[PDB]
Image (cartoon, rainbow, N blue to C red):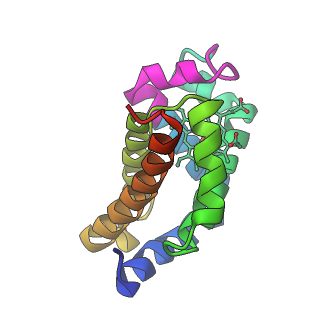
Amino acid sequence: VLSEGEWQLVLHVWAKVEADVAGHGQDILIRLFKSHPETLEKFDRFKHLKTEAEMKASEDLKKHGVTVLTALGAILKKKGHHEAELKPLAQSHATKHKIPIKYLEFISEAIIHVLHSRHPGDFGADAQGAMNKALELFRKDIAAKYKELGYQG
Ligand code: HEM
């Protein structure tokens, strides 16, 4: 489980992300798409983007980054008591968007990398370990909903 001190590390760095939600969101999605190109194919909205420069110039991509980080922040601020928020997300990602759990692992790695690049002083090893645990909890709870619906695999 996460301890109170671990949650405090997570939420202290998250308060810094919220001073620039759009910029963080852009960086995280670009990192995902460049490191794991198969993920771009799940987005009919974005699959025309071929270069990093094109990704950086897209306002629609920046808008989706804000949607993703706003939803994640709402989950993290519940400190584990996130059923109401998480259940609808799991349902749409399993049955409509068809996102494998592995791609949730990939985006979690992208989040960690961008937080370390933008906030080294508040993102030392202790904070990294707490954020990894928070994102593991997120994935574990989505995976349990996927299995109920027959999408875990
Ligand atoms: C931190 C993880 C993630 C969060 C919090 C998140 C959140 C959201 C939210 C709030 C929406 C809009 C409402 C909905 O459709 O449920 C959405 C849409 C979507 N997400 Fe996720 N997402 C995450 C990861 C991913 C990943 C890894 C992929 C693909 C590789 C993905 C693919 C999509 C798609 C295709 C849509 C629909 C976009 C559109 O065409 O409007 N998501 N996501």
Residue 121 locus on image (x, y percent): 36, 72
Residue drawn at (58%, 73%) of the image:
77
Residue 47 sits in quarter: top right
Decide which of 2, 94 is in the foreground and name it: 94
Residue drawn at (74%, 33%) of the image:
60
Instruction: Confirm whether the magenta stretch covers residue 41.
Output: yes
Q: Quadrant of the C terminus?
A: top left
Residue lying at the far bottom in this picture: please name it: 4
Is 61 drawn above or below residue 23 in the view shown? above
Instruction: Confirm whether the magenta stretch covers residue 148.
Output: no
- In-image side of 70 versus 10 (left or right): right
- Magenta-highlighted residues: 32-48
Residue 122 locus on image (x, y percent): 39, 73
Residue 98 sits in quarter: top right
Residue drawn at (73%, 42%) of the image:
63
Q: Quadrant of the N terminus?
A: bottom left
Is 54 drawn above or below residue 24 in the view shown? above
Residue drawn at (57%, 67%) of the image:
82
Residue 49 locus on image (x, y percent): 61, 17
Residue 26 sits in quarter: top right
Decide which of 15, 142 is in the foreground and name it: 142
Q: How many marks?
A: 0
Residue 76 locus on image (x, y percent): 53, 68
